[PDB]
């Protein structure tokens, strides 16, 4: 298992994520805090990543983040 | 019409698990390999930004739990 911090919006989504990853054997710390909104997150900048067999559609990526109700941004692995 | 959730940086096992979980919870999920260029700014930790009382669990303990993490999941919106 790994060390995982789950930060930002308090709510069912963040709690369920945290719960799942603890169930998978990770060491999970949850910190409630203020976050940017989806449009602000998009405007932080996105690094486009190609997936074999899929069109990498720049506008589709922009729209998916900007128009989300919730954005989960995963960093590290 | 369930909540629209974008998972960005979903290239790893943890991203895939999150995407799977949230679709099981009836959300409309778009998992995206493309990732934030500035991940730490999604939920930037500062004394003013953290909802946890700094008299109880201090800012340094908060900062350390994120610094020592292998993976940081930042949840934006709700």
Image (tube, coloured by chain):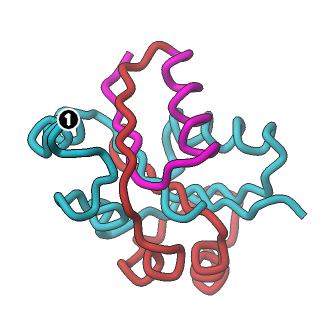
Chain colours: A red, B cyan
- Where is residue B66? Give x, y as percent: 23, 41
| Number of residue marks | 1
Identify the chain of the residue marked 1, using the numbered disc in the image: B
Q: Report whether B15 appears left or right of B62.
A: right
Assess disc 1: are there few (<14), some (14-19) or many (≥20) residues with their C-alpha within 10 Å of its C-alpha. Answer: few
Q: Residue furthest left?
A: B60
Q: Residue furthest right?
A: B1
- Where is residue B32? Give x, y as percent: 59, 59
Residue at image point 14% right, 45% down = B59
Residue at image point 14% right, 40% down = B58
Q: Report whether B72 appears left or right of A12.
A: left
Near-viewer residue (B21 or B36): B21
Q: Quadrant of the C terminus of chain A?
A: top left
Near-viewer residue (A62 or B49): B49
Q: Quadrant of the N terminus of chain A?
A: top left
- Where is residue A67? Give x, y as percent: 66, 79
**Residue B67, located in which quarter of the rendered image?**
top left
- Where is residue A71? Give x, y as percent: 55, 62
Q: Report whether B25 appears left or right of A23.
A: right
Seen in the picture, residue B63 relative to B56 is either above or below; the reply is: below
Residue at image point 64% right, 82% down = A63
Q: Dot 1: what SS?
A: loop
**Residue A46, located in which quarter of the rendered image?**
bottom left
**Residue B45, located in which quarter of the rendered image?**
bottom left
Q: Residue furthest front?
A: B55
Q: Is residue A11 magenta?
A: yes
Residue denoted by label 1: B57
Q: Is residue B58 magenta?
A: no
Q: Report whether A64 appears left or right of B59.
A: right
Magenta extent: A1-24
């Amino acid at each position: 298992g790994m060390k995982i911090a789950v930060i930002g919006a308090t709510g069912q989504v963040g709690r369920e994520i945290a719960k799942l990853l603890a169930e998978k054997g990770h060491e999970v710390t949850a910190i409630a805090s203020r976050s940017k909104n989806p449009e602000e997150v998009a405007k932080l900048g996105i690094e486009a990543v190609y997936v074999d067999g899929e069109v990498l559609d720049f506008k589709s990526v922009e729209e998916a983040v900007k128009n989300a109700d919730v954005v989960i941004s995963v960093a590290g692995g």
